Amino acid sequence: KVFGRCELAAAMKRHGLDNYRGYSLGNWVCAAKFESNFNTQATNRNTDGSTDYGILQINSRWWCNDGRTPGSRNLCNIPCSALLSSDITASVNCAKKIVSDGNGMNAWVAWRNRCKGTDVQAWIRGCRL
Image (cartoon, rainbow, N blue to C red; front, side, top):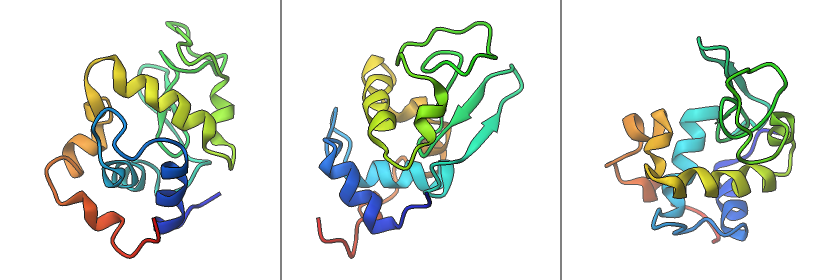
């Protein structure tokens, strides 16, 4: 599924993410836009054999198992595939873990380079929230 700006905001909110670990809702819509274009079915292979999955592009070397990344720790205890479903529950649940470990949303290349320190509230401007 390819989410709408607004609709994802609403949903991430419903799912406990507005100000989770101190990150505004916008920080999240932002990261997801530039990470997957609101498309939950997105995947991308990195050079190290790992692959990125879903709306929030969670990695398989650490967070989820997709049965073809060796180094692999499945800290989220979910099959990668789960993170591609039209329900974002699994992805949020897992994203909560990632963001709490230690590096905040720095764990996400794209948030850091294209989201961090910009007026992220602009992503939920217009929304019934």
